[PDB]
Every structure is written in C-alpha cells, then in structure tokens.
Length: 217
Ligand SMILES: C[C@@](C#N)(COCc1ccccc1)NC(=O)[C@H](CC1CCCCC1)NC(=O)N1CCOCC1
Image (cartoon, rainbow, N blue to C red; front, side):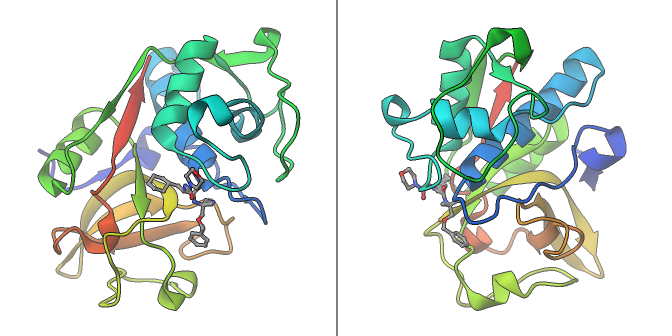
C-alpha cells in the first residue's frame, strides 16, 4: 500500500461544508464518500445534497435529520431511492424540511455499501488506498477537538464511543506521527481549512476505525 494518500490530490474531494446548528454530520459524511466515487466513475466532481438526506432518509432509516443519523442507512436510502440530488439543486438549510427529492435533479446513484471490520486500522488504510474516502465516526466531544489547529491530533481522554460523522480522505506521516486525514463539516474555520489530522495506529484513537463504511456506484 502507498505510504501516504490524499484524495484531494486526485480531485475527488469537494469543498468543506458548514453544517451550522443542524446535526447533519452523518449526511455530510455520506455525500462526501459518494462524491469521490462519483468523480472516480464519471470524471466529474459534484457536491451532493446533504439536505436531501436530512429531509428524506428519515424514520424508515433510523435517522433523525438535524438530530442525528447514520452514514450506512443514508447510503441504503440512496440505493432504495435510486438516486440523490445535487447540492446545487437541493441546498442545505440546516433545518429539517419536507422531503423534496426530484429525480430530475439526480446527480448520483449508489448500488451498495460496505462496512469495514471494527477497529482494524490496517483494513481502513487499505480501503482508503484502494477504494477511496471512507465515512467514519469519531469521538469528537472533547474540548481539544474544537480547538484543533495543526499537527496530529492526539487526545488522551478520547474514547471509542463515537458521536461525530466525518470523512477520511487520506493518511500519512507528519514529523514521525502517523495520521488519518479527516474532512469535517464545520466549515473552513475549523482546524486546517476544515480538516483534522487524527492519530493513526494509536490503538484506534477516538474510535476512528470503529465504524467505517464506503459506498460504490
Ligand atoms: C449529530 C451529530 C452530527 N452532526 C453530532 O453529534 C453531536 C456532536 C456535537 C459536537 C461535536 C461532535 C458531535 N452526530 C450524528 O449525527 C451521529 C453520527 C453517527 C455516525 C456513525 C457512528 C455513530 C455516530 N448519529 C447520531 O447522533 N444519531 C444516530 C441516529 O439517531 C439519532 C442519533
């Protein structure tokens, strides 16, 4: 496997989004993963509608919109629905709205998704290298997480009790510290222009490899 990977260098990652006061991290995590697959398949990089997921992949999928959801059930919604609209056609309002999906604005489809084995960072590395960005959940409730600015994030108080959906778009080594390159959805003001390098091969730090999954087209 390559020593380092950065899907941003392959034009497979869209701009960092700002979720605001709506707990739609799971939706942003899901579309980010599909966006990479879409690019890989069609050659075009297009942001997908996180709102579409918020408004439509709901109760039947065990999701609660601005109050939380799952990346895997979101993927299944896209599969069941036969598509997801583009972010441009169905803009993010950081609010729970009535489902307004319209296939005339479909920008991607999904045929299946895969959930990686719990806590295996070697398997996650392989997926990130061979398949593309992977949706994951991390424990982001520690004060240090919000204040992250640079370097490789390592928080002794972190746990494998995950609560925030984000996206791994690569991995590498910085000054002797292995890391996972994570795309967040708290805008460009957060961390490194919206990204955070989280400790890798440090005993599944913050549960990063606890619940990984990726979709395919
Ligand atoms: C709302 C949230 C998103 N957005 C942020 O959580 C609160 C929070 C606040 C600040 C910093 C970190 C986390 N999380 C979710 O949507 C998480 C994502 C999920 C991803 C897979 C692994 C488990 C976690 N889901 C979630 O909270 N629910 C799942 C569905 O029922 C409702 C609750």
